[PDB]
Image (cartoon, rainbow over all chains, first blue to last red; front, side):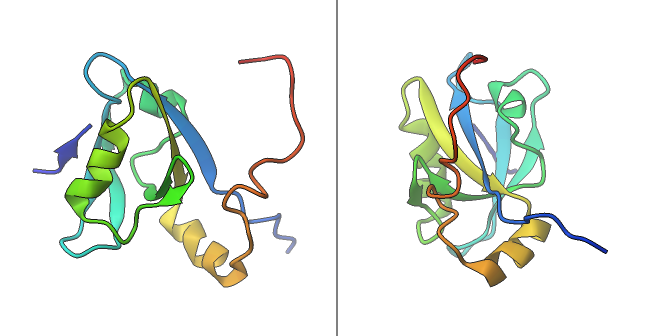
Amino acid sequence: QDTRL
Amino acid sequence: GIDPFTMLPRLCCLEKGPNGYGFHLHGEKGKLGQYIRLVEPGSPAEKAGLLAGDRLVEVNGENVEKETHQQVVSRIRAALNAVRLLVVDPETDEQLQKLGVQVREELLRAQEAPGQA
């Protein structure tokens, strides 16, 4: 689910 | 027509905001292929000039393409306050790769502009 930074 | 000097990977110094930098990076499950998926409108990332369609090539000056998706994200997270994200449009990258010059920092570190922050 994408990658949050 | 006349095309300008297409060889200008933009270095975005991303500030540690609330709990990160405020963008979603998507990566293909190999090595090389890390692209920005979505940017938070309330992030220090967007003001740094990071767009929701750029590719991350280097972190702080060193290439992070041959890493893993985890390691790429970890590179950015390893920064306490500020980290220099070198990003370029994947469309422009097509033109840039054909030039292959030392645009990595040599070109980026042009003349100085003392005044604004």
